Length: 175
Length: 175
Length: 175
Image (cartoon, rainbow over the protein chains, first blue to last red):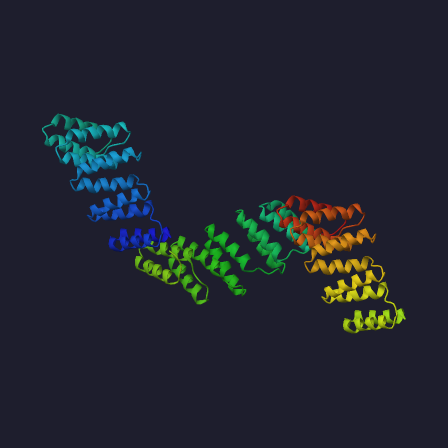
């Protein structure tokens, strides 16, 4: 039943043994044992960690078609694989979708996007999101702060970098 | 006579009306109408279902002193209340006693113990009992298999989990 | 004469030697020595005890045709063989006939019927008869009480079972 399969698939995915995990996945479906949320999340996360981001994205679509519901970890893993691969438009698109589904962004969500964006010259959108992060009562950190600070410094914007630096120390975030 | 009392006590215990069932029990003894095996089993099972496992255990002792004989249901109910309360040493002790009395463990007996043990890290004893279960010609199932499989997976022992998984499918036990 | 025959037939029937008892019966008739009430009752009771309830019923009919009168023992034996064989409609029919003949039901009559009925789900008729039993000034007992109590308990009707239980103890009938 789903519990036998989920435990094996989850253990194999943790060990990086994704070919076996995916095979048990396929086997599960064939026996008419129904994959659920946690089946999907474990596979997606294993594929994304292993560079196999196209297959992680297909499973995510398949998950949505079967009426199995994505959650903040689904979204965060995908958004993070996409952001790390330079695939920022698609990472932003999933961020907007997560919000339309009423699944709520958290600080891990904001940082990967801010960071990916600060990699392109997309500093104004990086800052816009940093702003948004706060107003949705989500709370920053050293990683967040440094990429903004490095972004702004790189772009000539020393005054605003120095100013985020002071804000950072007031918030108790350790430079 | 014992039949009037056993029927009322049994019906009250089934309805969860254990205070009344125990009162009729006490009344029975006072009139010198003798409680028997089935008097005891019904009370014990009702107490154990209702969380009242200390009183179930006292009745079980009382039963043994009065020369009324415990059987596999007595033992299974107790062992199962104990195992579900974390009280594994005492559950194991009753399992050994059941065997010394020549009352024979069955698949329900083995599963609760395997399961309780797989909850502690007691996976080797879980497996030892699973082994024993087979050699005394007692026959496993999905519940049995899954807790072992989940136990082994939790403990890094993926190869043995996968291997029980295949054994499970050969035996016609449906994952 | 009838006294020679009745004594032998009665003694043979008591010893279970029903083939010989029936043969002497037949012999009696052939000599034009007239069977009477007690001839019939002894045969019927022997046949009914020996499982030969169809022949007991035929003799009973024959008895009625010859103008020999059935009495409460005739009726009770038949009603009891019928009730014990599951043949409850016919047992009830003889009970009604006994009453129309002005032969009066007693506590043995009521118990077998109550009991047979409580075997089918016929608990309301069991209770109706228990009621009737009392109003015709016929007096209950442990057997009566227990089958009612067990009947009611089996049928979810714990409150009424417990209530008959208390009634039982007030009447001095020992549970």
